[PDB]
Amino acid sequence: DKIIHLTDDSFDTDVLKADGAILVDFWAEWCGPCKMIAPILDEIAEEYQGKLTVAKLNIDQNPGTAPKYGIRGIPTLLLFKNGEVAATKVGALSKGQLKEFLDANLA
Picture 1 (cartoon, helix red, strand yellow):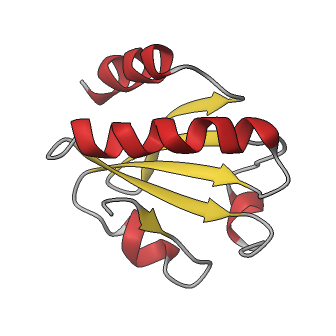
Picture 2: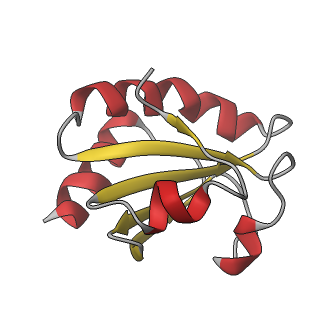
């Protein structure tokens, strides 16, 4: 609903050219930890309305983007502020951990 479903081609516009903070989720369908965090991202998108936007870029459907960010393990969450990576998180984490990751890095 509020999550951006990113593509290779749309990544520049949706992420790099966005005026504000984007939490990008690099994931794949076969990845268990990716799927466990997916409903956590859903809640993050609802609660952080106005502060950031959540966007996902499935790395099998869109194989181009992730190498540019040196992704080598999923899920990886990158936090962008205006096209620039501020904060990197690798592996699954809880809602309370992601929250703390966001709050601390959004400031």
